[PDB]
Amino acid sequence: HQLLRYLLDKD
Amino acid sequence: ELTPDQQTLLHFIMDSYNKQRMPQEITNKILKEAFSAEENFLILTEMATNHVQVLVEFTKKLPGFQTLDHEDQIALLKGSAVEAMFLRSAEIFNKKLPSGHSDLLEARIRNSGISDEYITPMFSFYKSIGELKMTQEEYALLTAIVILSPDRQYIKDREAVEKLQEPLLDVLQKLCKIHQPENPQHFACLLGRLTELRTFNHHHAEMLMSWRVNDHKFTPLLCEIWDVQ
Ligand SMILES: COc1ccc(-c2nc3cc(F)c(F)cc3n2[C@H](C(=O)N[C@H]2CC[C@H](O)CC2)C2CCCCC2)c(OC)n1
């Protein structure tokens, strides 16, 4: 789930 | 009556919830003209990709969410995404439209491409939501409650999620006593609706694969959230 991880960790 | 902190929480949840695509934007497209199952599948995947993106931003603004374990954060999103999509669809469906419009919208959805097997329970759930006569705040709080469900699979710290869900449940309960004082069963009815939401999540992949199309193309983001491709 690297896209979801990206969307959660982005400012 | 709501406290100053609860009133603050409610407006903050409302503003974040209002960042979604307008119901009218969605219903205008469906009502305007009839589309083939191929065009409707494409409309659905794009609508669902937008929904997931907007849901992640809504979820991030939920009080205490950013303090949770990162793996639990993902389990919560993966666990609620489909339920939140169907709850949003139920809201848009029960929004008042001119005479005959909601009859055409229902007929257009019935012939979208989805197999008849899933049509009846989907419209049953939609019509049950409509009977509740829910306000915009009730839909917003219920969506927040759906996302912050501690009884979600793979959750490591259930108590951490519980602490976040409880103040939202309290606000909803106060609004249910204010909005419908003649119906003291209203809060219980909304909580009951969440069990029906979970059934759609179990049959989500089949609903999509049984669509009347030759190829079922999904976006990389939808492949992560849905159990497809
Ligand atoms: C997976 O099976 C299915 C089968 C029907 C739907 C479904 N129910 C709807 C009820 C409405 F009242 C409505 F307006 C649209 C609705 N759709 C589609 C859609 O576009 N849903 C998005 C979801 C995310 C939001 O942000 C916006 C709406 C569907 C309607 C028919 C043409 C194609 C698109 C679905 O949505 C949950 N899932």
Image (cartoon, helix red, strand yellow):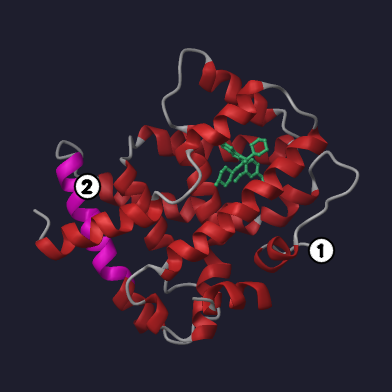
Give the foreground label among 2 and 1: 1
Q: Quadrant of ligand 1?
A: top right
- List the residue tagged with mark 2: B176
Instruction: Examine the structure image and report whether residue B212 is included in the region drawn in magenta.
Output: no
Q: Which mark is residue B229?
A: 1
Dot 2 crowding, Cα within 10 Å, few <14, some 14–19, many 20+: many
At 30% from the left and 40% from the top, the residue drawn is: B135
**Cα distance between the residues tagged 2 and 1:** 41 Å
The region drawn magenta spans B165-179
Q: Residue at x 67, y 54 (%)?
A: B204
Judged from the image, the secondary structure of the residue bearing numbered disc 1 is: loop
Q: Amino acid at mark 2?
A: Cys
Q: Is residue B101 among the parts visible in the rendering?
A: yes
Give me the residue at 47% from left, 49% from top. Answer: B20
Residue at the extreme front: A11
Relative height, residue B194 to residue A6 (above, below):
above
| Rendered location of residue B57, percent (x, y) | 48, 64
Tell me, yes or no, whether the two marked residues, 2 and 1, touch with CB atoms within 8 Å: no
x and y, in percent, of residue B114 in the image: 73, 38
Q: Main secondary structure of the magenta part?
A: helix
- Judged from this view, the residue extending furthest toward the top is B99
Note whether residue B82 is visible: no
> Which residue is more in the foreground, B219 or B184?
B219
Kind of element beneath mark 2: helix
Q: Amino acid at mark 1?
A: Gln
- Taking the image as shown, residue B22 lies to the left or right of residue B180, namely right
Magenta span contains residue B168: yes
